[PDB]
Structures are given as C-alpha cells and as structure tokens.
Image (cartoon, rainbow, N blue to C red; front, side):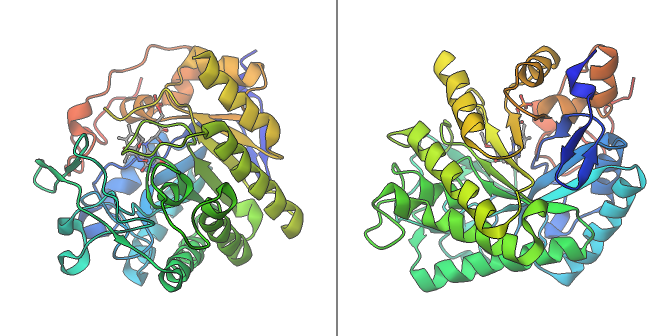
Length: 366
Ligand SMILES: Cc1cc2nc3c(=O)[nH]c(=O)nc-3n(C[C@H](O)[C@H](O)[C@H](O)COP(=O)(O)O)c2cc1C
Ligand SMILES: CCOC(=O)/C(=N\O)C(C)=O
C-alpha cells in the first residue's frame, strides 16, 4: 500500500492523503486582485481531503516584489478570494493562504511612490541576483530601508490583520512565509541581519521577529490554523547563515514554546529541502534533525518525486509532502501519484506570465 494515501489528522483537518499543493507565485492575480483564473487553477488541483497552500499573498501595499501577485489586505481582495475558496471547498479540499512579505527582495516599480523596500538591514541583495520586472526584463535589487521597532510592530500587525482577513474570506488557515530570503528570513539569517538593537546580534534576537509574527497570528486565529514555513539552509537571494542547523533548531524551540504557552499545536512546520533552487547526506540529516526536534506535523518540500515522497512518509521523515513544479503541469497530480501514471512536463517560460489560460489552466488531465 502507498503511504502517501494513508489518512492524516492535521489538527482538526482530516486529510485523506499526504500530497500537498506547495505555495507557488504564478502572477495571474492582475493588479493584486484574485481573478477568476485562480479559481479555475485551484479547482483543477483540489481533491477531496487534499490540502492546498496558495501562492504567496501580500499583507500590505509594501509587501510585493513580483507582478500581479494577490493581496489579502483590502476588502476587495477578501471578496474575490471568497469566490476562490468556495470552489475549492466544494471539491472537499482544505486550503491555507500563504502570507508573504518580500522585504528587500523588491524594486521601486513594486513599491508605493517608488519608495525603497524595507528590511532588517540597509544591505541589498547582491548583483548576482536580478529581479523579474513587470515587462519581463530583469532589474537591479535596490538598497532597502532598515526599519525601527515601531515599524516592526506595524508589520506584525499587518500579518495579524491579514490572517483575520483570510479567515473572513473562508480560508481554513494561513501559512507564514518565513523562508527563502524574504522579510522574515532577512531577520533570521546572520548573513543579512547586522542589527545592534533587540532584533539583531544574538541568535535569540534574530528569532524575535518570527516569534512575534507567529504569536500574533496564533492569538488572532488559533494555533491549529497557522502553519509556518522556513528554510534555514537555502541558496536564494543572499540569505545565508553561519550555522543553519542551530538557526533551524532555535526556530523550532520557539515554535514548541508557543504551542506549550497557547495550549495547542500549530497546523504544521513546512521546511524547504536545501537542494531546492529557483534558477546530500548533510541535507537529509538537517531535515530529519529539525523534524525530530519539532513537536508537531512536518511538511517537506523541494525536489520531491513520487518515489522520494513515498520514501519520506514511509521512513518517518515527514508527515506530508508538498509538490510544486509537477503540480503546475499535472492538475491531477494526486491521482497520477496514486495510479503511478506518467507525468506531464512543465514549461518554466510560463511560470510567471499573466495569461489566465496559457501555461496555467491548459495543462491536460489524464
Ligand atoms: C513557480 C514557483 C513559484 C513559487 N512560489 C513560492 C511562493 O510564493 N511561496 C513559497 O513559499 N514557495 C514558492 N515556491 C517554492 C514551492 O513552494 C516549492 O517548495 C517547490 O516548488 C517544491 O519543489 P518542486 O518544484 O521540486 O516540487 C515556488 C516555486 C515555483 C516553481
Ligand atoms: C528559491 C526559493 O524561492 C521560491 O521558491 C519563491 N518564493 O518563496 C519564488 C517566488 O520563486
């Protein structure tokens, strides 16, 4: 029997199988408003008892660094998300909204009034990386503005309000994007965070921001509706730490403590496999070390296949396995994995284009 199709209780959510739609930015949410195309896309991939995580979603007007990504900070956005959540729920799926602030991984073109993006630091991403522009060219990451503690508290409140908005739209929960060199990771990683106040220096201080964000959303909507994504070891946007495993374990310790204090477990911890990039024994052991340390559900992501996902669940390395690129090109990926049916190729050229159909909803079913 296939271990990916054993049921799993993710808190109060009864999942029928362990194949998860990973969060993926696709840039079809024109003008940051969820569009009907998103409803068709998520409906195609929804299954009864299956778990879906949305594309990263803006928590505020300054949180974007990609074109046409959805927000959930306005009532117009909430109204349009509600239509998408309804069609997914009609298929029996569980769906979480990923809350995403890019921090310094932005550009004047994505910021109100062309202002500088915000970060923990004034250090820019280096010129080894270039940002996708709305016209399909690539631009230069600018120097960010380093925020003070008042502004940090405002950003935490943006997460809190967005979590409440997600519940209003009908989402089952939210995921905190704390990975991949974006705003939260710019506080976590000692290769970025050069602060001398209470949010920088020590490992404890670098973990303060993610702790406050998670506590804020747990207080607002309940721990069992909150997932947290991190990537202590990742090659993306100059987000390195001198001791990735200790960083990961410090975050896990904080999450365990939040659960004890709240008297409830989070929905899950979601960790990117260090092998995953946008453009091996030590890697696997880092994943298992974090899993063994965390008191709760563990989702693994990054480079998984049918065989590797089966291995992960069978060996106890993870409870759930999220798939990205193969879910782009296989709307019925869950069914194909169950049947061991051949998978369709994906076309990177249309990952981030705006067409509501081409490269988005026109990948065929079996
Ligand atoms: C087009 C694309 C967009 C992505 N956008 C996000 C995102 O918005 N938030 C996030 O946490 N991860 C994002 N990722 C990472 C995926 O969630 C996932 O971890 C990765 O695709 C899994 O590896 P796989 O593609 O080999 O399955 C993205 C990946 C792709 C390919
Ligand atoms: C390389 C890791 O970064 C990602 O996967 C991502 N978002 O988190 C995007 C928008 O591609």
